[PDB]
Image (tube, rainbow, N blue to C red; front, side, top):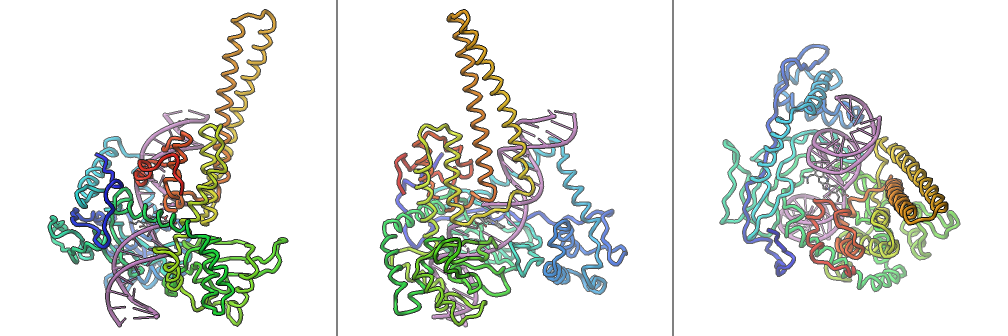
Length: 565
DNA sequence: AAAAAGACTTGGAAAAATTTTT
DNA sequence: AAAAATTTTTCCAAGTCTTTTT
Ligand SMILES: CC[C@@](O)(C(=O)O)c1cc2n(c(=O)c1CO)Cc1cc3c(CN(C)C)c(O)ccc3nc1-2
């Protein structure tokens, strides 16, 4: 069965579902204590830890190879959290982390990882079958007349928080999620999932205004985490289709918005000038609407509305270009945004006024926040927010670049190179940067030797065709002419093979510091890709893998080769 | 309001399983 | 067969925007 939810009458506003039934979450397996021979040492002397304290110790031991375990913040936060898990008898002995020895514990886990890759075919297939039967029973929920898959039904096991970038809470313990922390959401007429025996759920609710099945609060940030349906479901896919339709509606009114914000740079009021400059930044450079965050709780990262004076450096002339704004800051996930961008005269002049009488720690856009900006965007067009510009600019750039880089007469490997260069332009615009693959970038040597070995085969084939043509001169007959034909086809087959290898080598080189995944799955109206694939006869499986094909099932079925964003 | 909460949106590096070279 | 290069799951957070509290 294949449910085409996209052919149904669109789901009404307010209510998300009428019926909802699931078996609840799968809890992480219990902690298995260390055997007798794996010893922990404090001040050089043997010490057996209580299960609760031993568990927290194993987490640090497993991370001993990383440099972050030597960091002040990591160690401070870890030790404070490990103390809470210790008994009173253990707290009187273990005064500090530095006198502790986790070396035997670290070696054991490395030995287990080695003992696991040396498992038998009977053991390997068994664990794979235990995993598959867990997916049949708990990986599916029933939502309104249909069986839909659940994304992450297995709750993440306990461990140590690290986060991304320079996070103030690195080292902290992420405690084991218990049934007592779980809030279940289902309909009043559904069979309520039973908790593990000897346990109870925190709450069983019936809120049809939300899309989640299970929720709980995590101890690091104090936020609510959820278990929702998978990307191939109606509830996720319809909202994704709507996100793209909203981005298409912005397209038909973007010049009208551009002309107004350009005029708003000249306004009498400062709040209107700042709002217009911030809008320009979100449009031209596709910056995220930086929401304000609590200091000392998260890693110091900013976006457009949260930019500080220290994040921009103004230059009247740089590189022979007029009115350059040197952007240098950490955006989402602590990914550095560096750009030297030529702006209009009025923006540069406006930026000099927003930087007047301010200290480096002060906000560039005072009197402005994401709420004020989105309240204005909502008046310009219904349902328009700041992130819609990122979606619009990404999708329109993909469409225009595929239209400009794709050559009709090219073979499939060459067209995939044109597709990837177009996706690359989107990733550069969105700043989806990447650090060169951990050494492993020397796999460019391996590709070059295979290319040089193929250039050898081609050069040998050209010598065969050369002597076949010379043998066709002396004693010209229809038997020697057919040998020249077969040698020409042999040169042709080898030329195509080399072309494919050289195209793959270029693809990897240009993609060294670029991450394509995020724009491909979140930013890029899949219909633009489907339309391109059908137009040039490029099979969809060459662009989207199995999981992406399932998420974008709606676009693959409902989209002609003539679709225009 | 305007903080505080709640509810959605937005992988890539490392492992491991395979596959290919040797 | 055994080392090496690939293709595929496994691990682990952070923003945006909407809705409630204070
Ligand atoms: C790396 C790119 C990115 O950070 C991003 O913002 O551009 C991201 C992260 C994550 N995801 C994505 O789709 C995307 C891309 O759009 C899904 C995801 C799941 C994560 C989970 C799993 N949860 C949902 C159960 C974690 O536990 C920790 C971090 C996680 N990070 C991500």
